Image (cartoon, coloured by chain):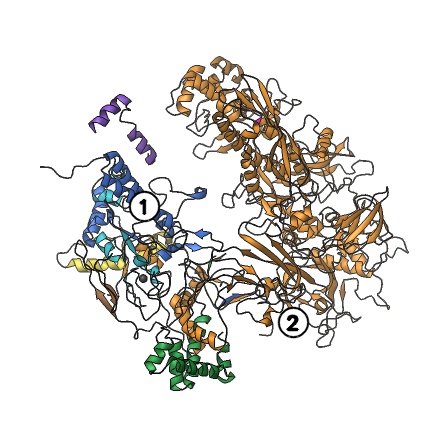
Chain colours: A green, B purple, C cyan, D brown, E orange, F blue, G yellow
């Protein structure tokens, strides 16, 4: 009679898969620089979260430029067009 | 049965005779 | 087996030798410790040791160096826990290297005494030999 | 009642391709049996080990 | 009758019952106050049994008194039990979850022998729980009732068997006492007499007889006529008291040195030194009566007397001799028989008093052990009973009894009757009795001694039939614990009014007549040939001179709940049993209409069930309000009775109490002053009087199904309020403290709207499955966030607030309003269990209406679910346009042998329309024996038929043919009892007249909303990975072994593989199945379950190499 | 002849299996995976053992103490007693209630050896391997429909 | 002797052993109750599940 409060919720796992897919599509709407900065900044490609200096190094620019592209991209995604699609997962 | 290992042990340890300070001194010196 | 299918076509029982046992085990428990009293994490070389029996957390070793999938199949060189999925603890076994031999209770006491026939001794007689209450001569010239 | 073994669960695809390359190290026991211990590449391999 | 504000309910009783119904809760209250020693029981003993007081507790203290050390230098005698006042009133204890108790004070006394002192104190013994006024213990805050148990009485059981190898009668005796030992005197296959003493390898008599001080010469002296004993004397094979007792010690104590003094002392120790042997008061009286040793001698000396041993042997050998009676020197002779283990002369009632006494003894003995051990260790001239007595054992024993026991059950209170019937319950399946597996099938049959001592009808119909019953109406429990029964003493063919109570033994001795006999208004019988009962249950026509006892009234054999069934004598015992077991399952409706047709037991079952406020002493009401009645007791004083409006019962039902008096009415003592849940003017009313027709209509009332008008739903005729309780505790945790606060991590302000500020809902918010009744947030600490989740959290600007949400949410399908919220907190000093800083209980409640699948039943066992609630226009209506309200089926009536419902139907109509006996030409013979003021009746006039002296069928025929028309000139129901119904749906009249009437039907507590259940994916068990079980969780339905056989028989292999792999256990397969369903793909191929891998690792753990090799 | 028959049975059984009865003398003893003997923590801190934890702990304690005594070189009395206790506890773990009174614990409840998980009516071999709770399921009370 | 064996195995064994020197094993039909019939199932798995 002991519910294991750690089991796979079934709907949670499939929901996470759907979130992965939808987020991937939305990020693919971003420009190449934008998609790259987002994926690296939030570790969507290897699970390692790269920080601003690493991202500026692998793109060969200054970290201030990386942060500006970051802010611009975030604001673009906050736009309801590509936002309301992902609201429900949260 | 005699399954009680408590008994199987107590009846075993009741064998060797009990000693005294005299024999204790002798034993300790020997040891 | 470790990896299973639905092609199972023969379930074959049979007594297991200790040689088969220390090749099953993925480690050896030696300390009668269940879980630390204060931090509530398994002990090393205990009855729940993650090194012996696999991680309690999905793709995380004990000391927390490797904590993601990209590190899988590897063993962290300091806490020794192999980073993998956390259901191996359902399947990895241990063993205990005894200091002296010991006998079963199923093939001896269960009527009829299979050992009792085997070595040609009555059950009650053997219940005095394998509980340390009678000597035995093994050979003579 | 509701209880759970103190622990955690992850929901991520078990990608079998893009991982961190390993490096199997041999560790001879006193009796001489060999027990493979996979280690990562950039990883200081210890001289001794509990097999 | 005899109750001031009695509903004027005209009875059909042809007879006249002399004795009133007793104090229906005396079996509980008198037993408990016997335990205490209340002045009430003191005066009761002064009346009957004034020989001496036995205050329960007192007896325990006296028997224990004193605790003497082995050295015999120090003695302790706790004595004079005393009770303080209850620490808190009832309602406060029930609200604050306190156990309603009162302290025990006892004068302990310690005495040193050598120097000489007494050390007297007043030691606090413990907080002892107390019976309420309603015969219940409020233990732990609930309402628990201790059910009386039936157990074999200590005594001598002479019984015999036959031997098919020899064909000889083999008699035997057992004397199983309390706290003693077993002894057997048997007569074996040969003509010898085994005397097996304490379970080990028999004995010849002579060993004991000499050891008992009886020489072979003395053996002949008393047993000369006993040719069997004389033959055994020849067979003695041993002589001499010393040698015999020496061989006793050598055998009974195997291998123990048979020294004379140890053996001599052992004889006493086992049988006469009363510290290891005590057949109690009950057994002593039993054996005294059996052997007739003593009559006026007070019941004392609760230990064996060797005088009785030799009498036992003599009685046994004369029983084998085939004697009729036996005279023992020093006592009046007794007759010679055997004994049965059912006859209520051998099964006694260990009432609540005796059970609590036994548990207190189990406590006191432990206390005594500890006391004496410490006394020995303690130094002398320094100690006192305060330093000796440990009161932990007594408290522990009483707690483990009231809580955590089989014989202390939650009072099932769905309706008041279920309360009064969970009391008065006899249960044979208790500790010290028999389990439902060791239950001899001879213990469940109604031995003919049950007549007037235990109802043969009412028993649970589950796997408990006969193990649980209920006391009769007039039964009364003897001090010793034997179920007495009142009878009328008939002398010189003259029936008197001097009620005399008799146990089962004197029921066997004497001869018993019937109450429905022609008494000729003088005590005189009329016909000489009279129905009567003999000893062995035989029924015989005795001449009317040898009758010495007559029954007090009919309906004496029957319980309380079954006596409320009208026309019971027409119903079969199966369906009457069902009717009695479902008359305790009705729910309290919002209107509570009294039954139009009933027995005399609707008023006496409410004024004594405790769920009706009673005017204690006469007065005039001043302020009648929905909460409080103020009565002005004549002599100055005033008293405010307080109601319990909308109080949750122990099964979720309402417990309202509304007054029935006005501000100027005068009340008398013992009057009903306020109805309870199921009551109307003081008469037990569990259901409504619904119009019923008995046609089979369109297959909706097919096979016990019942259809209803929509009038029942609309006008709120059948509607039960259910108050459910939810509870969340703010327990401490290692990571931090769980805070009941409004804010919750992801919970938006939309759902949060209900929560006020503390976290609790506001009284009145209509909660629905999923609402946040109490908002509690639990610390979680820092845990890794998946890259994807981190991205979303940042993009949408939502942070973590690691503290996790575990708020209480209303269970699935438990909507309704929030009647009240009760908050217990540690800051308020509320004594919550350790670790709980706050425990809040929310009482949600819903007004459930009748619904398809709800179970309705009459009073006759005619249960049935509601197949369909039809609209009001497609319902067969009369010629007047009045639609019928339910439509039962016909095919269920004749094959179930319960035509009671039909008679109840016809009489019901008669009682509604009102009759007028056409006595213009004199009272017709049809009513020649009918009482006065039944020659005419008014519409909706209440009537009653007692159970076994009810309405003779002829009376019903004539009444049915003598009803007055409704409003026009229209006799709707003709003499046959049927009426011409018009089909409401089609329109054409039905071609044949149909039975209509008013039947009283109830709403059972098997509602659909408590039963419907569904699961797609929910919680999972822990060790094995199957779905969980029960409606409290989600769980699934056990696809058991027999269903596996069923689908093997069809050949459905793929479905079996499904239901046993990827719906229950295939751990990695379930999530893949769900993902494939959502993505719209073929359901994946199932895998090995998780019950063929735990097995594999167990077999590789018991060292059995179980392996799978395809080849 | 008959006594030979019954003996003849088991001896040829070992001969034909070619299994070399050594399996009766149990050297290194295998330990069942942790999850099959869960230490669930019921909310409130109350831990829940599985009673196979306790038996395994007993065997391990006695083995450790035996190793210690062997190193010290205790007199034959103590070493033989401790070997006896090892044997007793291994026997208890593989079956509790056989070869003597049951090894009990709190409330004098007998423990649950591996055998009591694979025997009688509560073993896997007479239980959940008969019936299984299933998802995608429900129940309800039934009524008659003379329209379907 | 006294052991109970399936008929098909019995006849197949006799067919095998008439060659390599001929000797018949003498068999007699037996009637056993359903319980005993189940007890002689070959599969240890079902046998234990019983
Ligand atoms: Zn590590």
When the figure is inspected, residue C69 is found, relative to residue E1105, above or below; the finding is below
Regarding ligand 1, which quadrant of the image does it lie in?
bottom left
Which image quadrant is residue C134 in? top left
Magenta residue check for E310: no
Q: Can residue C1 be seen in this view?
A: no
Q: Give the range drawn in magenta.
A: E64-68
Nearer to me, E813 or E180: E813
| x and y, in percent, of residue E102 in the image | 65, 39
Do tag 2 and tag 1 residues touch (Cβ < 8 Å)?
no
Chain to which mark 2 belongs: E
Callout 2 secondary element: loop
Relative to E109, is E815 above or below? below
Which residue is located at x 36 percent, y 52 percent?
F118
C114 vs E502, left or right, is: left
Residue at the limit of the structure toward the left, as seen here: C141
Whether residue E891 is visible, yes or no, is: yes
- Disc 1 crowd rating (10 Å Cα; few below 14, some 14-19, many 20+) is many
């Amino acid at each position: 009679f002991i519910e294991d409060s750690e089991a796979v919720v079934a709907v949670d796992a499939v929901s996470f898969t759907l979130l992965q897919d939808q987020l991937q599509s939305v990020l693919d709407t971003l420009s190449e620089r934008e998609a790259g900065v987002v994926r690296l900044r939030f570790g969507l490609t290897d699970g390692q979260p790269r920080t601003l200096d690493e991202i500026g190094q692998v793109y060969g620019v200054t970290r201030e430029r990386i942060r500006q592209i970051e802010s611009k991209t975030m604001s673009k995604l906050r736009h309801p067009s590509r936002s309301q699609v992902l609201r429900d997962y949260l | 049965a005699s399954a009680d290992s408590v008994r199987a042990y107590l009846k075993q340890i009741g064998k060797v005779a009990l000693l005294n300070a005299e024999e204790e001194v002798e034993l300790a010196k020997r040891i | 087996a470790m990896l299973d299918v639905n092609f199972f076509d023969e379930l074959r029982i049979g007594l297991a030798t200790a040689e088969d046992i220390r090749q099953w085990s993925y480690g050896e428990v030696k300390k009668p410790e269940t879980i630390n009293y204060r931090t509530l994490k398994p002990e090393k070389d205990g009855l729940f040791c993650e090194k012996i029996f696999g991680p309690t957390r999905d793709w995380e070793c004990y000391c927390g160096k490797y904590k993601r999938v990209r590190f899988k199949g590897i063993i962290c060189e300091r806490c020794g826990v192999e980073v993998t999925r956390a259901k191996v603890r359902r399947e990895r076994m241990g063993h205990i290297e005894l200091a002296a031999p010991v006998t079963h209770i199923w093939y001896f006491k269960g009527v009829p005494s299979r050992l009792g026939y085997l070595l040609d001794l009555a059950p009650k007689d053997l219940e005095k030999i394998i509980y340390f209450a009678a000597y035995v001569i093994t050979s003579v010239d | 009642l509701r209880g759970s073994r103190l622990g955690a669960v992850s929901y991520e695809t078990d990608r079998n391709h893009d991982l961190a390359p390993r490096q199997i190290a041999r560790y001879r026991t006193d009796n001489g049996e060999e027990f493979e211990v996979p280690f990562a590449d950039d990883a200081e391999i210890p001289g001794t080990w509990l097999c | 009758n005899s109750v001031p504000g009695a509903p004027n309910r005209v009875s059909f009783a042809k007879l006249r019952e002399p004795l009133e119904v007793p104090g229906l809760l005396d079996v509980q209250t008198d037993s408990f106050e016997w335990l205490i020693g209340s002045p009430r029981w003191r005066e009761s003993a002064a009346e009957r049994g004034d020989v001496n007081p036995v205050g329960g507790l007192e007896e325990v203290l006296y028997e224990l008194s004193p605790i003497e050390d082995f050295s015999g230098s120090m003695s302790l005698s706790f004595s004079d039990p005393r009770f303080d006042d209850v620490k808190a009133p009832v309602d406060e204890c029930k609200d604050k979850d306190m156990t309603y108790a009162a302290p025990l004070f006892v004068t302990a006394e310690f005495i040193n022998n050598n120097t000489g002192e007494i050390k007297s104190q007043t030691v606090f013994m413990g907080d002892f729980p107390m019976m309420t006024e309603k015969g219940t213990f409020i233990i732990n805050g609930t309402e628990r009732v201790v059910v009386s148990q039936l157990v074999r009485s200590p005594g001598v059981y002479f019984d015999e068997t036959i031997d098919k190898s020899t064909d000889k009668t083999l008699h035997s005796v057992k004397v199983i006492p309390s706290r003693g030992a077993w002894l057997e005197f048997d007569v074996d296959k040969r003509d010898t007499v085994g005397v097996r003493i304490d379970r080990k390898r028999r004995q010849p008599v002579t060993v004991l007889l000499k050891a008992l001080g009886w020489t072979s010469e003395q053996i002949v002296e008393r047993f000369g006529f006993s040719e069997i004993m004389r033959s055994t004397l020849e067979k003695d094979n041993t002589v001499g008291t010393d040698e015999a007792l020496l061989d006793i010690y050598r055998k009974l104590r195997p291998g123990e040195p048979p020294t004379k003094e140890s053996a001599q002392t052992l004889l006493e120790n086992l049988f006469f030194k009363e510290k290891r042997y005590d057949l109690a008061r009950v057994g002593r009286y039993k054996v005294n009566k059996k052997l007739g040793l003593h009559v006026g001698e007070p019941i004392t000396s609760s230990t064996l007397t060797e005088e009785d041993v030799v009498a036992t042997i003599e009685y046994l050998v004369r029983l084998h001799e085939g004697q009729t009676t036996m005279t023992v020197p020093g006592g009046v002779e007794v007759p010679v028989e055997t004994d049965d283990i059912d006859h209520f002369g051998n099964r006694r009632l260990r009432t609540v008093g005796e059970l609590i006494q036994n548990q207190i003894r189990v406590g006191m003995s432990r206390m005594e052990r500890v006391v004496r051990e410490r006394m020995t260790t303690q130094d002398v001239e320094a100690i006192t009973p305060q330093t000796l007595i440990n009161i932990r054992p007594v408290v522990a024993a009483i707690k483990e009894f009231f809580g955590t026991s089989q014989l202390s059950q939650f009072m099932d209170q769905n309706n008041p009757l279920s309360g009064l019937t969970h009391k008065r319950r006899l249960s044979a399946l208790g500790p010290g009795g028999l389990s439902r597996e060791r239950a001899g099938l001879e213990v469940r049959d109604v031995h003919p001694s049950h007549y007037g001592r235990m109802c043969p009808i009412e028993t649970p119909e589950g796997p408990n039939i006969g193990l649980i019953g209920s006391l009769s109406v007039y039964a009364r429990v003897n001090p010793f614990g034997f179920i007495e029964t009142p009878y009328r003493k008939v002398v010189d063919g003259v029936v008197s009014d001097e009620i005399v109570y008799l146990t089962a033994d004197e029921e066997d001795r004497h001869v018993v007549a019937q109450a429905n006999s022609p008494i000729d208004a003088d005590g005189r019988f009329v016909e000489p040939r009279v129905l009567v009962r003999r000893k062995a249950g035989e029924v015989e026509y005795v001449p009317s001179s040898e009758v010495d006892y007559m029954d007090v009234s009919p309906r004496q054999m029957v319980s309380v709940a079954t006596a409320m069934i009208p026309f019971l004598e027409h119903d079969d015992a199966n369906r009457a049993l069902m009717g009695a077991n479902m008359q305790r399952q009705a729910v309290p409706l919002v209107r509570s209409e009294a039954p139009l047709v009933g027995t005399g037991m609707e008023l006496r079952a409410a004024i004594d069930a405790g769920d009706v406020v009673v005017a204690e002493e006469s007065g005039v009401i001043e302020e009648v309000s929905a909460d409080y009645i103020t009565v002005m007791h004549d002599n100055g004083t005033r008293r405010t009775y307080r109601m319990r409006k909308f109080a949750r019962s122990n099964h979720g039902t309402c417990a309202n109490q509304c007054p029935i008096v006005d501000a100027g009415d005068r009340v008398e003592a013992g009057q009903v002053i306020a109805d309870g849940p199921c009551t109307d003017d003081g008469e037990m009313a569990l259901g409504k009087n619904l119009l019923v027709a008995i046609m089979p209509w369109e297959g909706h009332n097919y096979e016990d199904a019942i259809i209803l008008s929509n009038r029942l739903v609309e006008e709120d005729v059948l509607t039960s309020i259910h108050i459910e309780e939810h509870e969340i505790d703010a327990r401490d945790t290692k990571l931090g403290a769980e805070e009941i606060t409004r804010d919750i991590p992801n919970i938006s302000d939309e759902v949060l709207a209900d929560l006020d500020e503390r976290g609790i809902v506001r009284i009145g918010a209509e909660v629905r499955d999923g609402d946040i009744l109490v908002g509690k947030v639990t610390p979680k600490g820092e845990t890794e966030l998946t890259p994807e989740e981190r991205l979303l959290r940042a993009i949408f600007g939502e942070k973590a607030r690691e503290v996790r949400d575990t708020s209480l949410k209303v269970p699935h399908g438990e909507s309704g309003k929030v009647i009240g919220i009760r908050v217990f907190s540690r800051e308020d000093e509320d004594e919550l269990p350790a670790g709980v800083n706050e425990l809040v209980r929310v009482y949600v409640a819903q007004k459930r209406k009748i619904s398809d699948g709800d179970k309705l039943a009459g009073r006759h066992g005619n249960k049935g679910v509601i197949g369909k609630i039809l609209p009001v226009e497609d319902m067969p209506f009369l010629a007047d346009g009045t639609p019928v309200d339910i439509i039962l089926n016909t095919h269920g009536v004749p094959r179930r042998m319960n035509i009671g419902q039909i008679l109840e139907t016809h009489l019901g109509w008669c009682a509604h329309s009102g009759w007028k006996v056409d006595a213009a030409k004199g009272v017709p013979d049809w009513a020649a024996r009918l009482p006065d003021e039944l020659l005419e009746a008014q519409p909706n006039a209440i009537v009653s038929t007692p159970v076994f002296d009810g309405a003779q069928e002829a009376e019903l025929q004539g009444l049915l043919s003598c009803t007055l028309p409704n409003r026009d000139g229209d006799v709707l129901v003709d003499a046959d009892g049927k009426a011409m119904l018009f089909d409401g749906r089609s329109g054409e009249p039905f071609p044949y007249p149909v039975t209509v009437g008013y039947m009283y039907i109830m709403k059972l507590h098997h509602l659909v909303d408590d039963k419907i259940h569904a699961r797609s994916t929910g919680p999972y068990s822990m060790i094995t990975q199957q779905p969980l079980g029960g409606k409290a969780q989600f769980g699934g339905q056990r696809f058991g072994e027999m269903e596996c056989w069923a689908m093997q028989a069809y050949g459905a292999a793929y479905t079996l593989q499904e239901l046993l792999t990827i719906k229950s256990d295939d751990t990695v397969g379930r999530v893949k199945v769900y993902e494939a369903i959502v993505k719209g793909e073929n359901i994946p191929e199932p895998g090995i379950p998780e019950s063929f891998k735990v097995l594999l690792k167990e077999l590789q753990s018991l060292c059995l190499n179980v392996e799978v090799l395809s080849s | 002849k008959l006594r030979a028959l019954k003996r003849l049975k088991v001896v040829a059984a070992f001969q034909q299996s070619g299994n070399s009865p050594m399996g009766m003398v149990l050297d290194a003893v295998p330990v069942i995976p942790p999850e099959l003997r869960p230490m669930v923590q019921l909310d409130g801190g109350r831990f829940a053992t599985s009673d196979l934890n306790d038996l395994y702990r007993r065997v391990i304690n006695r083995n450790n103490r035996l190793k210690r005594l062997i190193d010290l070189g205790a007199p034959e009395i103590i070493v033989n007693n401790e070997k006896r206790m090892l044997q007793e506890s291994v026997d208890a773990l593989f079956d509790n209630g056989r070869r003597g009174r049951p090894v009990t614990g709190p409330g004098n409840r007998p423990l649950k050896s591996l055998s009591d998980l694979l025997k009688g009516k509560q073993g896997r071999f007479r239980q959940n391997l008969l019936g299984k709770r299933v998802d995608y399921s429900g129940r309800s009370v039934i009524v008659v429909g003379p329209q379907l | 002797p006294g052991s109970l064996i399936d008929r098909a195995e019995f006849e197949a064994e006799n067919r095998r052993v008439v060659a390599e020197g001929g000797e018949p094993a003498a068999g007699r039909p037996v009637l056993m109750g359903i319980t005993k019939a189940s007890l002689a199932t070959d599969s240890w798995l079902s046998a234990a599940s019983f």
